[PDB]
Every structure is written in C-alpha cells, then in structure tokens.
Image: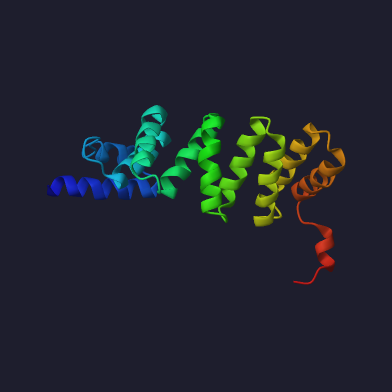
Amino acid sequence: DIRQVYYRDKGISHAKAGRYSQAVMLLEQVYDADAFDVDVALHLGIAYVKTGAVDRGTELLERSLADAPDNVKVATVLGLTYVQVQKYDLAVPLLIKVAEANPINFNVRFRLGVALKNLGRFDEAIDSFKIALGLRPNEGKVHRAIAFSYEQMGRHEEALPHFKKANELDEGASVELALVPR
C-alpha cells in the first residue's frame, strides 16, 4: 500500500504546487474510477486540464462533482474550465451556484459575467458585473466589460462612465484621489 500512499500524497502535493506533469505521472498510478477518491480525482483532473488533456480532465471533474455535489472547489474549477473552453452554457449553472455559495469570490463573479455576456444575456451579465465591482471597484476589466454590455442594450448613458473609468484606470492612478482622505 505504502508505495501507492506515497504516490497519492506526492501527486496531490505536485498538483497543489503547479507541477502538473508530475502530478499526472504519479496520480495515474493510483487513480481508480471504481473506488472513488475525491482528493485524487480533483487534483488529477486539474492536472490533466493544465497539461492539455482537457476532455479527460473534465471527465474526472464531472465525475467528482457528481459524487460530491457539495464540493465548492470541484464546482469552481469545472465551471471556470468550461468558460475557458467556451462551453458557456455549461459554465453558467455551475458558476451561478458557486457565486451564491462563495459570494466574495470575485473571480467567479467576473467569469460568470463574461460567460453571460458571451451568450448575449446582456442584462444578467450587467447584474453580475455590478456585484463584481462591489467587490473590486478599481478593476478596469469589469468596467470595460459592463460598458460593452450596456452598449449592446443601447444603454449608452449608463455605459459611458464605465468606459471613462476603464480608460482612466488604464492611464493609471486617478487624480481626484489626491483630495480624498483615507
């Protein structure tokens, strides 16, 4: 058992550090679809995704979510991976739940917004981006993405201040802060 237990621990340790090739090498040796180990599948799944074995990765992740429906971390990376591969309709349901479940995860909220915007759900997108900007008011990329969503609905007045903020955030440092106490 001991060489197998070493490989599990070392493989997980590798997945956690970004040593994905090695994480695959070790954890393939110990993975078993027949007797589920959710730690092994999550980390091997991530590892497969990051080495370009995306279909095999997502499979492990889908199987892991099915088996532990409550695992926020599995849901998260599955959701985000589908956004990455432009499977937006799959991402959206996953990310909707994660965001409600982890309401300070800004990245999730932003990506949800991006997926919703790609699908042309301009209104829902705008809703998610506002929550996002409540979390991080000075993220230029949300201001830009929400301005584009508004613009597509013809809501130009609403877009404009966001277009301007995004541009000013690019240039850097906002001059008016010079007169705002901390």
